[PDB]
Amino acid sequence: QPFRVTLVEDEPSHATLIQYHLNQLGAEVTVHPSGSAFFQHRSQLSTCDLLIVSDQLVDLSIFSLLDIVKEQTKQPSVLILTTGRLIESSEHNLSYLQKPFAISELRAAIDYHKPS
Image 1 (cartoon, one colour):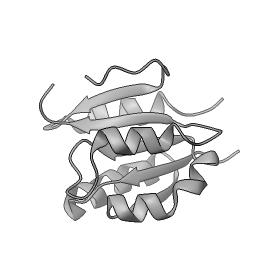
Image 2: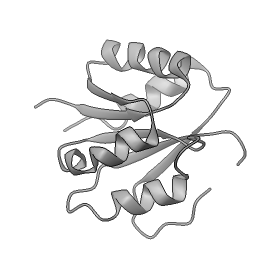
Image 3: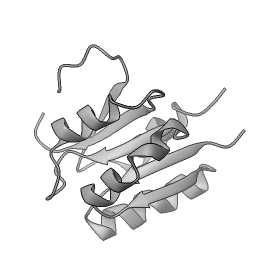
Image 4: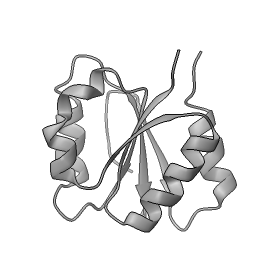
């Protein structure tokens, strides 16, 4: 099976860097350059295995974003790229990675959310 990853990130240089490593770890990646891009494709999260989202999209809060994910009938694992330092959820699928991060951490993270 494929490892479908959706990347929602609005700094294009962090997005392209993350996308490069996703492709080296063997992901089929969908990149949404904004929160509005993500919203208009809400529906395709039922086929996503891992959602990597920034904590600080200029046009959608992580809270709204996470509540939109919660409306879907199949929810992915979520990896939240953060600065500050942890959102209280009772779905158990939020993991976090703090920027600035080492590339090794990014890749361990992504690999620990692969199948099977």
